Image (cartoon, rainbow, N blue to C red):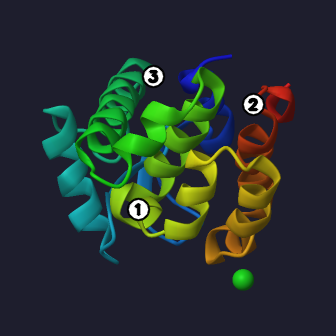
Amino acid sequence: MNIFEMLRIDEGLRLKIYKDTEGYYTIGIGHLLTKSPSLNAAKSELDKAIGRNCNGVITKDEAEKLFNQDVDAAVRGILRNAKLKPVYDSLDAVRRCALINMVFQMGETGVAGFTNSLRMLQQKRWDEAAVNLAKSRWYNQTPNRAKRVITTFRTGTWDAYK
Ligand SMILES: [Cl-]
Ligand SMILES: [Cl-]
């Protein structure tokens, strides 16, 4: 298991514009297109993103390309973030995957907001951090995915995904 297979399980793949769990226009492997209510504003961003007239639809390769950019951008945002970088650097390889997953889903800013949990992970207090991570809108809104991520931080293995 790697970051790609992990995210592909949590986000799935859809080749047609769809609405995410928040109701935002998305496509591919969790690639947010826009928070705007308009399907046309979504079709627009989509074509801008791919470089062709897609008319709301893309190919597998196009989805995988967006996915490769988004993972890279997620890592690069963590590395550039003063609050995140030190956490990331302190973590083992599996756990790093768990942080990247949160970042991909909720953005740098959002994760950077879990001050207490971040401190606990840095300190390697596993069980405590799993408990604090669960007290969040994130966990209440997408509980099966949050549990998977949280188990990953708790144990440091891929069990939740196997
Ligand atoms: Cl809560
Ligand atoms: Cl869920």
Q: Can residue 87 be seen in this view?
A: yes
Q: In which quarter of the image is residue 117?
A: bottom right
Name the disc covering residue 60, or none. Answer: 3
Instruction: For label 2, count other residues whose C-alpha is less than 10 Å away and answer few (under 14), some (14-19) or many (20+).
Output: some
Q: Residue at coordinates 43% horizontally, 32% vertically from top-left?
A: 89
Which of 66 and 144 lies nearest the eye of the viewer? 144
Mark 3 is surrounded, within 10 Å at the Cα level, by few (under 14), some (14 to 19) or many (20 or more) other residues, namely few
| Residue highlighted by disc 1 | 112
Q: Is mark 3 on a helix, strand or loop?
A: helix
Of labels 1 and 2, earlier in sequence is 1
Secondary structure of the residue carrying numbered label 2: loop
Quadrant containing the C terminus is top right
Query: Quick one: SS at disc 1?
Result: helix
Q: Which amino acid does label 1 sit on?
A: Ala
Left or right: 52 as drawn, with respect to 65: left
User: Which residue is at a point 79% across and 44% down the rendered structure image?
Assistant: 154
Q: Which amino acid does label 3 sit on?
A: Lys
Taking the spot 86% from the left edge, 28% from the top edge, the residue there is: 159
Residue at image location 56% in from the left, 47% down from the top? 122
Which residue lies most toward the front here?
Answer: 123
Task: State the residue in front, 23 or 88.
Answer: 88
Quick check: 76 above or below 151? above
Alpha carbon distance from label 1 to label 2: 21 Å
Relative depth, front residue between 114 and 126 = 126
In the figure, is residue 33 to the left or right of 15? Answer: left
